[PDB]
Length: 25
Image 1 (tube, one colour):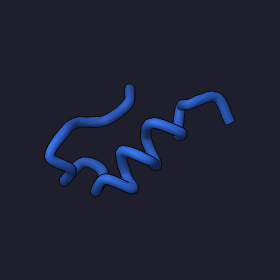
Image 2 (cartoon, rainbow, N blue to C red):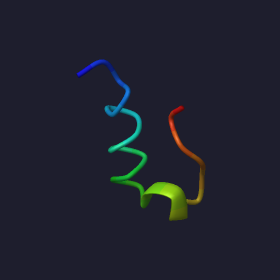
Image 3 (cartoon, helix red, strand yellow):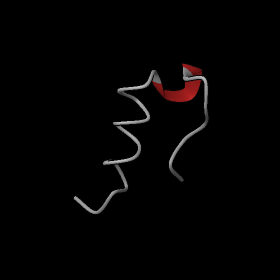
Image 4 (tube, rainbow, N blue to C red):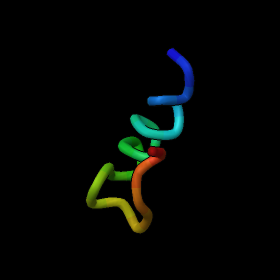
């Protein structure tokens, strides 16, 4: 991957679109 994901999935590891944050983008 490209950290399309690795900040994402990972953001998603954080809880995705329901994280305390928002997506990688």
